Length: 238
Length: 238
Ligand SMILES: Nc1ccn([C@@H]2S[C@](CO)(OP(=O)(O)OP(=O)(O)O)[C@@H](O)[C@H]2O)c(=O)n1
Ligand SMILES: Nc1ccn([C@@H]2S[C@](CO)(OP(=O)(O)OP(=O)(O)O)[C@@H](O)[C@H]2O)c(=O)n1
Image 1 (cartoon, helix red, strand yellow):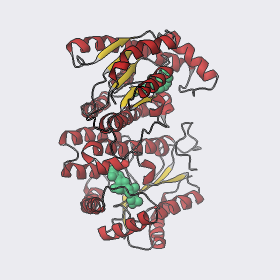
Image 2 (cartoon, rainbow over the protein chains, first blue to last red):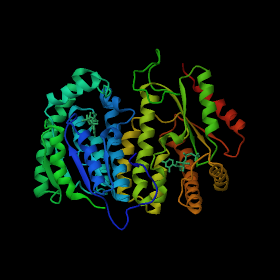
Image 3 (cartoon, chains in turn orange, red):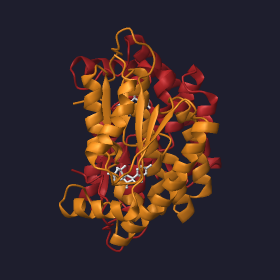
Image 4 (cartoon, chains in turn yellow, red):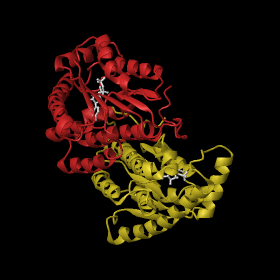
């Protein structure tokens, strides 16, 4: 529908360079999909060649093995998340000049490798190889232009996940109820640290040209849309 | 059909460990698909949980951009070939104990990065990052047990490719007739060197427990099947 995998030539009129790049940053079941789909449609209405990319686009067929056999599959499935996200951005954002609304940016994947390194599922040597490739890939992708910091509390994530799994609107990704609870909590803690890093790197680090926006994951979806649209509308190019 | 992406539990009876691993090694349009599909069916008939994997399984949606925009897409598309092959082997051969008949083994992908490094499409720094990840991935996969060296001459490859493209039985992967001709020739030269390396490493290197089998890419498909089956039938486990 959104022409995400077109290997044909760029069609951006007279506008040169990459499109613009909006990303949500937060733990699972933060309430992202209504937001990013609405934003992509409103940016298109303003004349932007914009697309919204749900993270489910990047779910490998083998995703569940990351969580049921993590010391075997966490390293290559983490490579898959960063590689497939990279390729989609390199083609759509950079090569074809389109504007992206992402449920997760290329800057967030490293924290998921950190989680598996701490648990022991990914070795230090695997992490070093990952980081070498990640640095080369990320150097070819512009920083996100607007990052929405939206980290849900763990019990909110788990309530939303439980309802979605019960009604069959998403699959059961974890090997046990406790594995789901534990990964959600470990990711929550890492995301709190990552967002504090973001606040620093937007002032004294590599993101001084990027806008950060804080957003409560428990806010109503209409409030989320209104808050993020007020900043995203400014980024429209034809 | 062959249950290649099953994240459910192993079902191998009392047999432990990985399955066995047969790979063809040669340039494009060597005449591989009839061979590997016939071999997988005959191994299954003998009671092996065997599968044949065509290389088209690993073609990324963005494959054509490797060849039309190589200095942007050769590095990540080469990462995709080795990552997707790795995951399929890690699940089917190792985790689930199945026997594989592959159109290309995990040992051959590095030569395709070498081609792009020589041309300048992949930088030396990108190649080093690739090699770091490749070493970690390959350390988790058994060597192939039987490698069939089948490298076609370039004009034979190009005649077969031209007929397949003309009748629509495969897509036109290259941006020009000359790009197709040139990549086929550069790969041919690299494969001749790779096969000479293979002959050494099966005696004095890391493949002393692997069988090599020479096969003319211009031989009739019935001769190919008979020659390879005479060695592959020995590798059947129930
Ligand atoms: N590098 C990464 C990126 C994502 N994930 C999983 S993939 C997942 C599935 O639910 O999250 P989603 O991004 O798809 O969004 P959602 O749950 O809020 O709807 C969730 O388990 C993430 O931790 C991961 O392990 N490694
Ligand atoms: N690491 C790799 C592996 C494969 N290829 C391409 S993918 C291709 C498409 O035709 O070959 P196939 O393996 O799919 O088999 P075939 O042509 O004989 O039918 C051919 O261009 C290969 O060089 C590549 O660039 N990098």
